[PDB]
Length: 60
RNA sequence: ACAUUUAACUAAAACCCCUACGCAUUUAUAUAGAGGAGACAAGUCGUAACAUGGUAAGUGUACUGGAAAGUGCACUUGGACGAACC
Ligand SMILES: [K+]
Ligand SMILES: [K+]
Ligand SMILES: [K+]
Ligand SMILES: [Mg+2]
Ligand SMILES: [Mg+2]
Ligand SMILES: [Mg+2]
Ligand SMILES: [Mg+2]
Ligand SMILES: [Mg+2]
Ligand SMILES: [Mg+2]
Ligand SMILES: [Mg+2]
Ligand SMILES: [Mg+2]
Ligand SMILES: [Mg+2]
Image 1 (cartoon, rainbow, N blue to C red):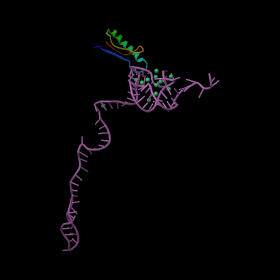
Image 2: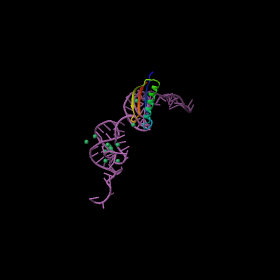
Image 3: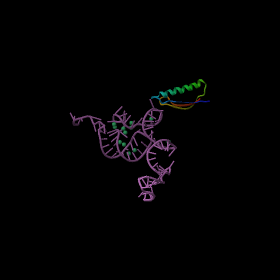
């Protein structure tokens, strides 16, 4: 069954470390879909204010 | 509500009421639902305060606004006015 994957930047500390790290994780799953030849369909994508990700949703 | 009797050549016998409490009063627990306060985050919106915080802040009171808060009158310094003259 297909997976609707969602990543959210947890509110645990100051700065954009949580939001910046979310972008890296989201790119990791997107690249992992290509490695497994999986179709990666973007559903939601809300970038942060410092080149990061607040929350993102995608379908694999 | 309720009666002084019997007996008395030594002296004794007899004596025995019925009405209250209604889930009425008093104090708590449990709550359909409606809110508050503290803790917490960093999410969302703005930047009110702390420097003359960029409208100096605040008190009382009134009205208004998503939200801090905004404005009127009076008061306070828990602000300043640069401290000879020019
Ligand atoms: K908040
Ligand atoms: K003010
Ligand atoms: K002040
Ligand atoms: Mg209740
Ligand atoms: Mg301000
Ligand atoms: Mg001024
Ligand atoms: Mg201003
Ligand atoms: Mg001000
Ligand atoms: Mg005032
Ligand atoms: Mg007031
Ligand atoms: Mg006004
Ligand atoms: Mg006016």
